Each structure stands twice: as structure tokens, then as C-alpha cells.
Amino acid sequence: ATFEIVNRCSYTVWAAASKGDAALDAGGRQLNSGESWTINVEPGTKGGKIWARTDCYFDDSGSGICKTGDCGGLLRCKRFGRPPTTLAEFSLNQYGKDYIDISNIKGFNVPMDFSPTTRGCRGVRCAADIVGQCPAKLKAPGGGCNDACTVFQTSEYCCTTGKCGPTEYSRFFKRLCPDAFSYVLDKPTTVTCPGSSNYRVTFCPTA
Image (cartoon, rainbow, N blue to C red; front, side, top):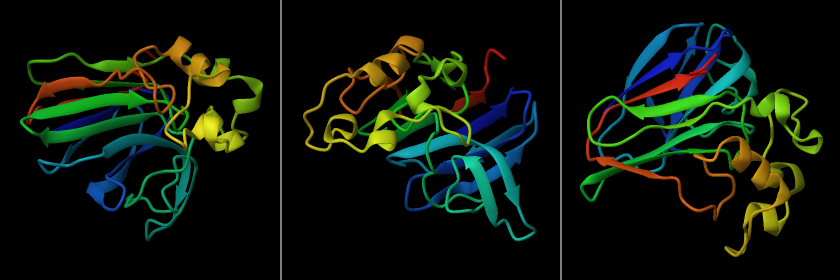
């Protein structure tokens, strides 16, 4: 499946793509403002994610640090990134179908649209200014808006027992972005697409 990742933000981002224990495609690449990077993701990929990382420094071997979404200091991500990270999440060819969503469960750094480029389903988007409006206690001094699990490490925010409810913090993300997951048991905003669809992830789709 092809995912065209487009950076419409006015700042550089370093895109990242991983299924948690492996890179997808090259796993990561710099995207200056306006640049598009097309990756290939193997059919059947389950629990894949794409995100942006901000304010990265890498040396000549691809080792360094990002202020958001850092994936163990690598340019080419092999593992998931450090919160806060707005997440494009997908499982492809799962019994005939693809499933996509956007999640704020690991916080928010960059606004995102995640849409099919082929027929048969709608895209999802979380493009509101969550960083500017972020509650004081969730603001990440590094940049971005942390989820409450990351900040407070409770059973209730992290949904550790499988039995949690919405919270004042989850409701803030859900208010600004109704179409993204705001906590682990949120009512699903997953979109079912035809198996083997292709997609585009656009950072800052409205700015």
C-alpha cells in the first residue's frame, strides 16, 4: 500500500513510520515545508503508525534527538516515538478490510489529516490548535500537548485495568478533535476502508 506523507506545515518535520517492532519503509525522513515523501507499507501490516517529529537534530549517521516523537534517537524509526505525538494508526488487509484512525491517546504535537487516496471510505482529521489551547498541566515543556496518562501515570488515565471512563483531560482532546480517539476506551472513530486502499497523511492540513 502507498502512503503519501505531505508536510503542509510552515516548519520542517521528520516523518516517522513504524509498527512498533520494525520500521515501515525507511522508517523516517526529513520533510521540509511542502515536501511529499511516498512510502510503501506491506499488505497485512497490523498496528502501523505514522507521526511527525519536531525540532530534530541528526548527525551524519542518522543519530540524534527530536523534541517530540523521538524514536530512540534514530532518523529512521524502528520503534514508536516519544509522546506527545498525534498518531495516524492503521491495520491493513484485516479479513478483507483496512482500518484507519487518528489518536490523541499519546498526546498531540502536529495537526494531521489521514485520508484514503482511493475509493470507498472517508478520511479523518484532527486539525484544531490543540497545542495553543492545551490545558496548563498537560503542556509539554519540550513542545506539544501530552496525554494525561503520560503526565500522571494513573490506572484511570492509562486504562490499565481495562475499565476507565472519560476524564476532564480526555474531554479536552475530544472537544477539539471529535474525530480522534481521546482515551483508550473512547467510542471508536475508526474508519473501515476497502482492503488494500492507499492513503495520504497531511501534516497541518488547514495551515
